Image (cartoon, rainbow, N blue to C red; front, side):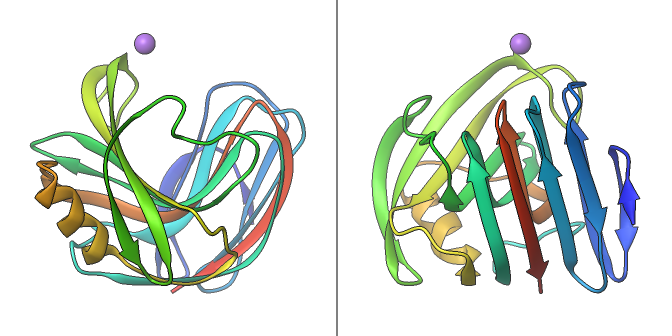
Length: 190
Ligand code: NA
């Protein structure tokens, strides 16, 4: 169903839907691991389905249609605790590349594409445990796609080899994120 911001479980999958207070976003949970989002001149929002908690060896499948009109990501997205980390394995994106706001540490060739690996520090920013300073890890896929499988271990291990430590996993979803843009997306996770 179309729901308001929050977290929970739907048809066997964890979901999280968050936004910054700006309107224009409609997030809808569908059957199984499906969800859809339509946004018209939103602010920042993140919504998707997956698992609570995630694991460090999950092979995540996703498929659907992704039509961003501006700044947006389609990623495997999640958090760890001790250390507190917000991470992304970006499979597709709109007009804004994460490389802008981040620093590059290396590359990994995974699931058919090279990904560039970055770290950034979020200072005094919102998080799963409230306002906090924490690191952000990124793998950004060079060849954008709308379906396939992501072997998360490929990325977590590559990050580790670059000195990026991950804590105990909290949630792990396939999420559509938007940032002051418009767009539409419909995705099934498994
Ligand atoms: Na801040």
